[PDB]
Image (cartoon, coloured by chain):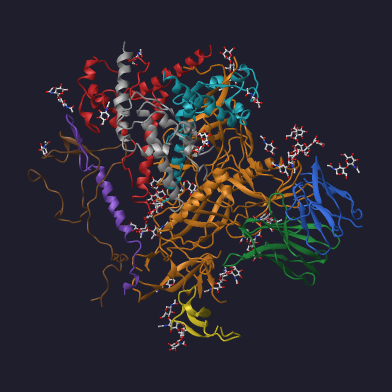
Chain colours: A green, B blue, C orange, D yellow, E purple, F brown, G cyan, H red
Amino acid sequence: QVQLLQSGAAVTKPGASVRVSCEASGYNIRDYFIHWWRQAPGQGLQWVGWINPKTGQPNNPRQFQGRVSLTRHASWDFDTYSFYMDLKALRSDDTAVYFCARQRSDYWDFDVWGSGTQVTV
Amino acid sequence: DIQMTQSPSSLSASVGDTVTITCQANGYLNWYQQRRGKAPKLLIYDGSKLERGVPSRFSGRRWGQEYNLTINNLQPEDIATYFCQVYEFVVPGTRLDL
Amino acid sequence: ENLWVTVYYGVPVWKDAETTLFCASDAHNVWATHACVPTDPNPQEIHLENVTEEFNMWKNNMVEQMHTDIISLWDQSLKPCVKLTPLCVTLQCTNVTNNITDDMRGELKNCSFNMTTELRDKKQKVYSLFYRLDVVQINEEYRLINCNTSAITQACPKVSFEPIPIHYCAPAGFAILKCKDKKFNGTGPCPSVSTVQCTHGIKPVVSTQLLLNGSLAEEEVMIRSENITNNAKNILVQFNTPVQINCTRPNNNTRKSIRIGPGQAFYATGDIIGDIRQAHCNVSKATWNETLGKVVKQLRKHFGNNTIIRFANSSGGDLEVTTHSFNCGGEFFYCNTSGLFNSTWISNSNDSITLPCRIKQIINMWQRIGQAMYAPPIQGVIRCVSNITGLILTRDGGSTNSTTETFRPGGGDMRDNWRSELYKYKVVKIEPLGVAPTRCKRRVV
Amino acid sequence: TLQCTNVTNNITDDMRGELKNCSFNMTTELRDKKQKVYSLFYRLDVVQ
Amino acid sequence: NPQEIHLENVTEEFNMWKNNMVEQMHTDIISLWDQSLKPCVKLTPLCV
Amino acid sequence: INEEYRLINCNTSAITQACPKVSFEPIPIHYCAPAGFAILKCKDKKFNGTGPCPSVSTVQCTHGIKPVVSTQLLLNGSLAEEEVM
Amino acid sequence: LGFLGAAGSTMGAASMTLTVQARNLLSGIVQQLTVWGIKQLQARVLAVERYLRDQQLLGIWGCSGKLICCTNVPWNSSWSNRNLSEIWDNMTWLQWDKEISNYTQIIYGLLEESQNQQEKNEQDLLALD
Amino acid sequence: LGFLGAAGSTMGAASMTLTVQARNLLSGIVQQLTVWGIKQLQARVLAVERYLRDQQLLGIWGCSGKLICCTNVPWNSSWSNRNLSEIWDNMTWLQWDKEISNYTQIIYGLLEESQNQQEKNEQDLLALD
Amino acid sequence: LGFLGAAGSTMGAASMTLTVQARNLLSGIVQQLTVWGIKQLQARVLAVERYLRDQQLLGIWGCSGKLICCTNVPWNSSWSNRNLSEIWDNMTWLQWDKEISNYTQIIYGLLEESQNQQEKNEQDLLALD
Ligand SMILES: *[C@@H]1O[C@H](CO)[C@@H](O[C@@H]2O[C@H](CO)[C@@H](O[C@@H]3O[C@H](CO[C@H]4O[C@H](CO[C@H]5O[C@H](CO)[C@@H](O)[C@H](O)[C@@H]5O[C@H]5O[C@H](CO)[C@@H](O)[C@H](O)[C@@H]5O)[C@@H](O)[C@H](O[C@H]5O[C@H](CO)[C@@H](O)[C@H](O)[C@@H]5O)[C@@H]4O)[C@@H](O)[C@H](O[C@H]4O[C@H](CO)[C@@H](O)[C@H](O)[C@@H]4O[C@H]4O[C@H](CO)[C@@H](O)[C@H](O)[C@@H]4O)[C@@H]3O)[C@H](O)[C@H]2NC(C)=O)[C@H](O)[C@H]1NC(C)=O
Ligand SMILES: *[C@@H]1O[C@H](CO)[C@@H](O[C@@H]2O[C@H](CO)[C@@H](O[C@@H]3O[C@H](CO[C@H]4O[C@H](CO[C@H]5O[C@H](CO)[C@@H](O)[C@H](O)[C@@H]5O)[C@@H](O)[C@H](O[C@H]5O[C@H](CO)[C@@H](O)[C@H](O)[C@@H]5O)[C@@H]4O)[C@@H](O)[C@H](O[C@H]4O[C@H](CO)[C@@H](O)[C@H](O)[C@@H]4O[C@H]4O[C@H](CO)[C@@H](O)[C@H](O)[C@@H]4O)[C@@H]3O)[C@H](O)[C@H]2NC(C)=O)[C@H](O)[C@H]1NC(C)=O
Ligand SMILES: *[C@@H]1O[C@H](CO)[C@@H](O[C@@H]2O[C@H](CO)[C@@H](O[C@@H]3O[C@H](CO)[C@@H](O)[C@H](O)[C@@H]3O)[C@H](O)[C@H]2NC(C)=O)[C@H](O)[C@H]1NC(C)=O
Ligand SMILES: *[C@@H]1O[C@H](CO)[C@@H](O[C@@H]2O[C@H](CO)[C@@H](O[C@@H]3O[C@H](CO)[C@@H](O)[C@H](O)[C@@H]3O)[C@H](O)[C@H]2NC(C)=O)[C@H](O)[C@H]1NC(C)=O
Ligand SMILES: *[C@@H]1O[C@H](CO)[C@@H](O[C@@H]2O[C@H](CO)[C@@H](O[C@@H]3O[C@H](CO)[C@@H](O)[C@H](O)[C@@H]3O)[C@H](O)[C@H]2NC(C)=O)[C@H](O)[C@H]1NC(C)=O
Ligand SMILES: *[C@@H]1O[C@H](CO)[C@@H](O[C@@H]2O[C@H](CO)[C@@H](O[C@@H]3O[C@H](CO)[C@@H](O)[C@H](O)[C@@H]3O)[C@H](O)[C@H]2NC(C)=O)[C@H](O)[C@H]1NC(C)=O
Ligand SMILES: *[C@@H]1O[C@H](CO)[C@@H](O[C@@H]2O[C@H](CO)[C@@H](O)[C@H](O)[C@H]2NC(C)=O)[C@H](O)[C@H]1NC(C)=O
Ligand SMILES: *[C@@H]1O[C@H](CO)[C@@H](O[C@@H]2O[C@H](CO)[C@@H](O)[C@H](O)[C@H]2NC(C)=O)[C@H](O)[C@H]1NC(C)=O
Ligand SMILES: *[C@@H]1O[C@H](CO)[C@@H](O[C@@H]2O[C@H](CO)[C@@H](O)[C@H](O)[C@H]2NC(C)=O)[C@H](O)[C@H]1NC(C)=O
Ligand SMILES: *[C@@H]1O[C@H](CO)[C@@H](O[C@@H]2O[C@H](CO)[C@@H](O)[C@H](O)[C@H]2NC(C)=O)[C@H](O)[C@H]1NC(C)=O
Ligand SMILES: *[C@@H]1O[C@H](CO)[C@@H](O[C@@H]2O[C@H](CO)[C@@H](O)[C@H](O)[C@H]2NC(C)=O)[C@H](O)[C@H]1NC(C)=O
Ligand SMILES: *[C@@H]1O[C@H](CO)[C@@H](O[C@@H]2O[C@H](CO)[C@@H](O)[C@H](O)[C@H]2NC(C)=O)[C@H](O)[C@H]1NC(C)=O
Ligand SMILES: *[C@@H]1O[C@H](CO)[C@@H](O[C@@H]2O[C@H](CO)[C@@H](O)[C@H](O)[C@H]2NC(C)=O)[C@H](O)[C@H]1NC(C)=O
Ligand SMILES: *[C@@H]1O[C@H](CO)[C@@H](O)[C@H](O)[C@H]1NC(C)=O
Ligand SMILES: *[C@@H]1O[C@H](CO)[C@@H](O)[C@H](O)[C@H]1NC(C)=O
Ligand SMILES: *[C@@H]1O[C@H](CO)[C@@H](O)[C@H](O)[C@H]1NC(C)=O
Ligand SMILES: *[C@@H]1O[C@H](CO)[C@@H](O)[C@H](O)[C@H]1NC(C)=O
Ligand SMILES: *[C@@H]1O[C@H](CO)[C@@H](O)[C@H](O)[C@H]1NC(C)=O
Ligand SMILES: *[C@@H]1O[C@H](CO)[C@@H](O)[C@H](O)[C@H]1NC(C)=O
């Protein structure tokens, strides 16, 4: 299994931060970028950005610069990876559901997805 | 740059018959199917192939800069949203219903 | 008349293939170039008229073999050195405040601990200086930073880290083609091919954000990438005029030596003779700002003619990829390049810049985690001068409306460092047997 | 040296004396500190 | 069968102290000596 | 240890223990040459170290040499035939 | 010229320099642990095995010890049909190799028996008189 | 005699025993880690590589499968000038090799192409009539 | 048939398939630490060494590059005496090899020098006219 476990829902006041996690369990973790997507009520998807898990390097669009932080962490048995997304200055528009996704090749074909986590303000 | 536009906002065909959805997309292309309150799932990548573990009712073909998604022998559960993505860009999908 | 088959042995024909090249060098050091056949004083090169071949980097197999070969030589040189297992103990540290500036406030620690002597039943009390990037507080007493992930190992301070030029030669029955086009892309047909017996002298220097001590282009600045519209691919820039960068470690270091058991020595760090100042690198502000101008002209050709082009500093990650990391004379630097990539170029002084650097001693060279290494201190004062001959960039995604592209420095994967030197070569296999029709027929007797 | 007792929590009588609950002192990652841990062992692997 | 052939009418030049069979007998028994010490007991606890 | 003892090597090296079922007895050894090579042999009785040997001969490999270690006297070796050399 | 120069020229002019391509098929490392110890040693054994597989073929067809060897198999036009001058004067060995790669296995079977095994027995039953 | 006996004799009488020297160029270790494991394995590969560099040369000159091979190159007296009897009856192969080692590279070039490849194409142009 | 089929048949009918046995003497490991690292490497060197020991023999007897090569040595009846039909039509190479293993070393000496070296010097004495 190549599951991508995700954490539960959360809600908070404006002007606060929020962290959402995503586990990787059943494959060679260090060989596939990890992307974060966002879906608003009654809209299409939106690219939040990607992270390279070997070096840990992020890439975000100009809309989210200075507000999003993508990080990762492994354990001293090196089997489990935990990816984190942190959002800093929340507003009403950030009410959405967020998706962990695992790229597979150079077509950007995302075969595995996470359950998704709903968060609102 | 990247251009992308798809063409039935939402059709309303019924059980049995077949329909097609067309995306115009410069540059690779994929198709996804997403039920309400669920994570999407990949059907067709690179515009022509299909992912291992999908009924063969779905199949797509390309010509020029226009791609086609079409499903044969509609089923009571194949009603969901369908959109096409290129790489960061996606589009608001289409809705079909009996 | 009816033509017959005739057989030819030794026709010029070749296909693509993979093999194991062997290496050759000139005339002790980590890359073990004392187990390389000595090179020859005759670099023979043959030009091939009227023939155009097809090159493709990012699939060249000479790169996947240079990688695994210097990862194997690195381990071969650590097998016989000292294991530092007794060094994971509890340390008792204290700030160093003896004639420091104010930038080095908190960068050095003076730690004391209990060590094993040459007798299994005696201990000794010992001190040594450690950098802040190598110790952690146990409960907010310190400990080395690696003692919950890996074991450290370092001796053999008679082995140097200086890179040595290395030629990669091909066995019999194979050949190495070489593209002599001056405006060559990554892939595509090169119409001015030529053959050699082995490549030029390649230096295995490792670095992260800038490419150092490499080769230059002859016509202008080149920009190579596979699918420049895919923002998950790095970009390789190559200058045509070098930029100098002078780096130094201005402290006067001393080196103790502690007999930990029989025949084992640990090389600590003694006191410092003088003042404690920070390490840095100075770059000429005029030359740098000029070559950055010559890069945006070529960068504009791939995007619209009136686009805004920005440079920003790295956005995050590990310490190795968020800074310019290199090795100068046995010490490992990590310099803050946030003063080089800070500008905005739209269409239509005479001093230097100073980049502050840090230093580490516990090194985890390739992303492998289960085995770190220590690095003994160097006596005296460090100083080196290098050429900057390229960059590794990364474009910000999600850019619509066709304006304001943003680039940031990247790196991390050493294979991109080898592709900047082996983009001209490819390996082919000779097929010397061919048949053809002709009029002669064998004489029956 | 281990210090073992019998496992009698919800067993049949086939397993009376087949499992032991042993406790001992182990070395940690810092050379001067130890830890006290435990583990279950089959009776065919320990001797008095 | 230790064969040996006599060669009439031929004289050759010998020179010890430059013979290369000597510099190979040396390094080959220095190397067999260490091969027989690799797999046996290390006396580390004896330095007390 | 100070003017209590210690082994003499504890400040220069470590000791291994001369694995007890392996003997130190020397055994004759013949050194043979690969294909395409040959081993010449001088049969002069009064042969010097260097110089022209006028009674050459060829063999496939040498006589049995015992690898005996010693310092001031050579032991269990070969003798001269005519006189002391 | 030198190694692989005639690769530019046409078949007629390139088939006068076979010896230079033939001489560089054996060695060139004239005088000279696993890394760089067994790396090389694995190469030198493959160079010999690839060289002996071609001397064996040339011997089976009756061409041993030669560089040009007129055989006795007729050229079926189904393999190609181009005027002789349109082959030896306006194309190269690189071009012609791609136009023929589909039939060499068909041809190689003929050379092996359609001449030599057929002829090796005839001289046997002819020298008996 | 045996292996290398004729080394004493003159060229005329020593050129009757070529097979003796030729047979001992391949093996003699009839039936049989790094020490004594990787050195010997590098000995057996060098013997094969050295034995094939000589068979390749003999084939290029048109002499494959022979021990004495009359060629078609004339003997330039600038290499040496001694009466035929003063060569085959009063000196040895050891003596003559030193008197000639300066010109072998000159001679080897004449045999390779300037005689055989010149001759290999003429039969090609002749068998097409 | 295939590799070693004719092993069942008689010598006459089995001597039509020599190429099948001859082709399978070189490789079979066509494509890609000691165990399974030096196991292979010790085998590939023995196959090359055993293959060159027989090409050398054939060249010494004057049969280089051939599969059937009748010589100039007469058949002494002391080795065997059976009607030619009682050899080529009612027995096999396996049966016949066991009847001759005592004399091959005697025969091999006659082929080597007593026929070819006796003949290789006579073309010399003839070609000098
Ligand atoms: C990209 O490429 C770049 C180009 O290659 C590369 O840069 C090069 O990097 C290497 C590696 O870091 C550099 O090589 C090192 O250079 C060190 C400096 O050597 C120079 O300075 C020495 C000191 O000179 C002072 O003292 C002399 C008396 O001895 C005086 O004569 C001098 O005038 C000078 O006096 C000044 O200082 C006095 C003391 O303070 C003062 O009294 C006085 O008034 C005045 O102010 C010189 O000795 C030395 O000379 C060497 O080189 C010249 C040629 O320039 C030769 O002619 C000489 O024969 C001699 O070889 C230089 O001028 C070296 O010290 C250093 O060597 C040490 O390390 C190596 C390797 O480990 C050892 O083999 C070597 O022996 C040294 O180790 C030893 O050190 C200690 C103390 O000596 C010793 O006890 C110990 O046992 C140990 O063995 C090394 O070679 C090179 O310089 C860089 N090039 C440049 C142009 O800068 C760059 O790194 C590359 N980038 C990347 C990323 O890879
Ligand atoms: C980065 O990654 C991206 C992917 O994300 C890469 O994009 C790829 O870019 C290449 C080259 O830029 C594209 O190849 C080109 O594809 C087009 C379109 O192909 C479709 O249409 C073909 C028919 O098109 C004609 O007819 C239609 C109407 O019928 C018209 O609208 C068109 O304008 C045309 O007139 C059709 O034949 C194709 O199917 C065939 O090909 C595919 C494979 O592509 C097969 O699977 C099919 O089975 C079938 O065989 C397809 O449906 C082609 O039209 C282009 O043809 C050019 O190149 C030919 C050589 O192969 C050449 O013979 C043609 O004459 C033509 O020449 C071009 O250049 C001339 C220069 O003077 C022009 O004058 C001329 O007008 C023409 O433009 C070409 O094959 C890829 O499709 C594209 N992939 C994707 C997914 O977008 C990008 O390359 C990467 N970059 C880097 C640096 O790596
Ligand atoms: C870094 O520190 C070391 C250690 O102090 C410095 O080395 C020292 O350099 C001085 C001056 O070159 C030496 O002084 C000399 O002393 C002798 C007598 O010993 C005297 O005859 C000379 O005239 C001179 O005064 C000193 O010996 C030397 N120390 C050692 C241990 O060698 C070094 O110079 C410092 N480096 C820098 C860049 O400051
Ligand atoms: C890499 O270098 C850059 C600049 O070269 C570093 O950013 C600089 O960080 C310092 C320390 O936090 C900032 O100084 C602060 O300035 C404010 C305003 O005067 C003052 O109130 C503070 O007390 C402090 O002095 C400095 O402003 C900042 N520069 C910029 C342009 O933001 C950066 O931190 C370095 N990277 C790392 C990892 O340290
Ligand atoms: C990255 O680039 C920006 C823009 O070039 C740099 O900010 C600029 O820094 C200079 C030097 O301090 C400022 O000049 C001086 O500023 C003070 C107060 O800001 C003013 O009173 C002086 O008269 C003088 O103009 C300049 O104002 C400032 N620009 C802005 C918009 O803040 C920045 O320092 C660069 N970062 C690095 C790490 O180099
Ligand atoms: C690369 O291709 C070019 C283009 O074909 C070759 O240049 C041509 O080579 C031919 C062959 O030597 C020349 O023909 C000559 O014609 C004159 C006049 O009839 C005749 O007297 C000569 O004996 C010879 O036949 C031709 O002039 C020359 N140039 C052209 C066609 O413009 C070139 O040789 C090729 N190089 C290689 C290395 O293959
Ligand atoms: C090994 O122990 C260290 C000691 O804390 C762990 O350090 C982490 O360090 C980073 C940055 O220094 C902090 O952000 C983390 O919070 C620290 N960990 C914890 C649990 O607080 C380090 O993670 C340990 N290594 C492993 C593999 O667990
Ligand atoms: C995708 O499918 C549609 C039909 O569902 C195709 O549109 C038809 O194209 C043909 C030409 O081949 C025309 O004759 C029809 O009139 C079109 N139908 C309509 C309703 O306009 C379309 O061509 C397909 N896409 C591709 C790239 O072939
Ligand atoms: C080195 O080991 C000695 C052990 O003799 C340590 O000294 C002990 O420190 C503990 C710490 O609380 C005290 O409780 C003991 O009473 C001390 N023993 C003696 C004999 O004084 C010493 O701390 C160790 N050194 C370091 C740097 O940790
Ligand atoms: C690091 O701390 C040690 C103490 O453990 C310092 O060593 C002492 O230095 C003073 C200086 O006057 C001497 O009087 C003491 O005798 C030293 N003690 C020992 C045990 O050597 C050392 O100087 C400190 N180093 C730095 C750079 O601050
Ligand atoms: C683990 O080690 C501790 C040592 O601290 C052991 O506890 C000691 O046990 C001895 C019995 O021989 C007592 O005399 C000491 O008084 C004990 N010390 C303390 C501090 O309690 C303990 O028994 C060991 N654990 C096991 C399972 O053997
Ligand atoms: C060694 O040399 C001697 C003389 O140099 C040879 O003896 C003569 O050999 C010739 C050649 O057959 C005979 O005709 C003479 O009768 C021999 N005796 C003389 C001249 O006194 C001897 O044959 C040589 N031996 C070898 C093995 O070459
Ligand atoms: C196996 O042996 C049988 C008989 O011993 C062979 O069958 C005969 O073969 C001869 C030729 O060898 C034919 O002329 C006969 O017609 C065959 N049939 C009979 C005698 O009944 C058979 O060919 C042999 N098989 C092989 C593979 O050699
Ligand atoms: C060292 O100094 C820093 C501030 O400069 C302080 O926070 C820290 O507690 C000090 N540590 C010690 C061991 O003195
Ligand atoms: C290099 O590649 C780019 C993009 O594929 C193309 O625009 C350019 O023309 C190429 N250069 C050459 C010399 O073909
Ligand atoms: C042997 O050596 C001695 C001294 O080295 C010399 O006097 C004597 O002449 C030599 N003998 C011969 C036969 O060369
Ligand atoms: C030539 O080949 C074709 C098939 O490609 C075959 O039908 C024909 O019989 C062959 N001709 C001869 C003479 O073998
Ligand atoms: C013989 O060699 C000499 C020396 O180079 C040369 O001058 C002469 O032309 C040569 N003669 C022949 C016929 O080769
Ligand atoms: C045949 O062999 C016998 C047995 O050795 C022998 O007596 C006889 O002379 C040989 N015949 C010939 C012609 O050699």
Query: Is C201 located above or below residue H109 in the figure?
Result: below
Q: What residue lies at 32% left-to-right and 58% top-to-bottom? A: E34
- Image-quadrant location for residue A5: bottom right
Relative placement, left or right, of C251 versus B75 is left
Q: Is residue C9 visible?
A: no
Q: What residue lies at 52% left-to-right and 29% top-to-bottom? A: G112
**Residue in the foreground of this view, choosing between C216 and E9:** E9
Query: Is C157 located above or below residue H16 in the figure?
Result: below
Q: What residue lies at 71% left-to-right and 49% top-to-bottom? A: A107
The extreme left residue here reads: F83
Location of the C terminus of chain G by quadrant is top left
Residue G111 position, x and y percent, is: 54, 27
Query: Is E20 located above or below residue A38 in the figure?
Result: above
Total number of numbered discs in the rendering: 0
Q: Is residue H75 visible?
A: yes
Residue G84 position, x and y percent, is: 61, 17
**Residue in the foreground of this view, choosing between H116 and C54:** H116
Image quadrant of ligand 19? top left
Residue E31 position, x and y percent, is: 31, 54
Residue C445 position, x and y percent, is: 46, 17
**Residue in the foreground of this view, choosing between F39 and E47:** F39
Relative placement, left or right, of A96 versus C225 is right
**Residue in the foreground of this view, choosing between E9 and B29:** E9
